Length: 123
Image (tube, rainbow, N blue to C red; front, side, top):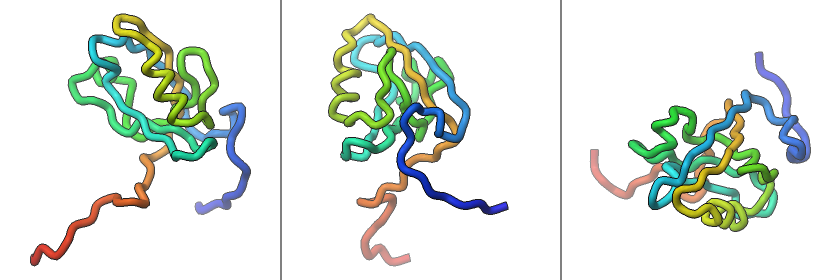
């Protein structure tokens, strides 16, 4: 039924709970057909913030939203800064490809800033 919780971060990715899967996207013009979020902090799990509709990530079927970034190309990044990980994505020029390993079973982040609000509309 219900069950407990505790722990102290991941490390070897092995302590995540989910499936593990991968894709190779070739960087076609512009940039990959998804965008990322990371916690700001230098040990928060990075996630796909969105998939671009009609983008190559969507056309490979495999990229989904909320998915947790474990590794990029062949680098362990699951606690790296979104500063470094965004630099890692930018380090790939157009027409090259990278591997990505995500973990599956994680939801999207709840956004503590604004997850969905509005002001005094009547209704």
